[PDB]
Image (cartoon, rainbow, N blue to C red; front, side):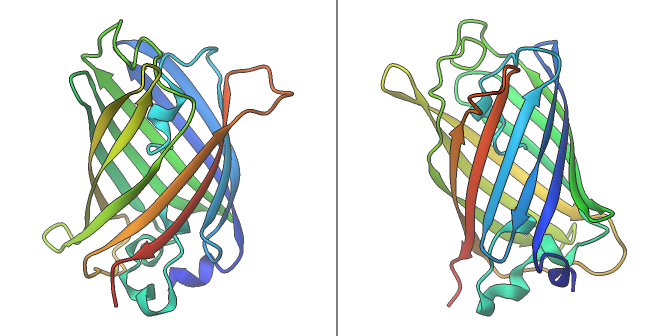
Length: 225
């Protein structure tokens, strides 16, 4: 079991290659993951200067193998069973009445480090919309992430909507269609339906001058008796 791999606080590296409406950018992240607790701490920096999109819009794109699966759930944990060979995470994110993000990532162990490498392509945003106009609050809400087994592809099928709060007191929904599929030949662990409970909290390093985002994530699995 790759569950034996998350026994401690694992180190995390995130590399995202990006392009939204042709605006290229790149972000690097680093931090650590305690799956036992159910907790991530990550910090990100735009290395091409300014991020052309609000930071909150990439939180879900920037490692669900650090979800805390209670003891009677531990076998619905595809995310870890797929390790250290890892898996591929593919998504489409439709921002309601605005553009979309299309992401492919590989999440696998690269030594002791758990690494998430992301290709993101984003099209059809409105330059004076909520996303390209930077009208989102620098903050994040609490969501459930709903997980189904997809034996067909022998991976999973995940869905949820993010509720991005808008300056004007409004909500911008972002609808996530997600699938994860195993990299290795050595069998993933297909789950009964459950959900992950995700609270994310967003901050700034007062000493960091580059465009960055600090992230604290708390996740714990749930739904099964």
